[PDB]
Image (cartoon, rainbow over all chains, first blue to last red):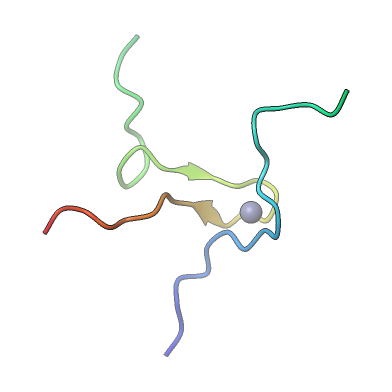
Amino acid sequence: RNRRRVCKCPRPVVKSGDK
Amino acid sequence: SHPEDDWLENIDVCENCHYPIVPLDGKGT
Ligand SMILES: [Zn+2]
């Protein structure tokens, strides 16, 4: 009926940067 | 040091949405 209201992120935080 | 098991199986809560972030569970059977 309804799944556990857990994390629903369209891009989880990963150990990395952007530079 | 010490085991990192303190959340229904060393789970962590994603502060991003407050909803618990669990890992793919496909073993144990
Ligand atoms: Zn999340």
